[PDB]
Image (spheres, rainbow over the protein chains, first blue to last red):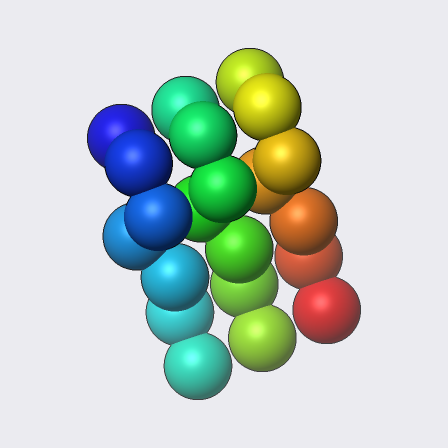
Length: 7
Length: 7
Length: 7
């Protein structure tokens, strides 16, 4: 994956 | 993975 | 992985 961020 | 960050 | 950071 590229740049799957969690907030 | 590239750049999958968690906040 | 490259640059998968955790906060």
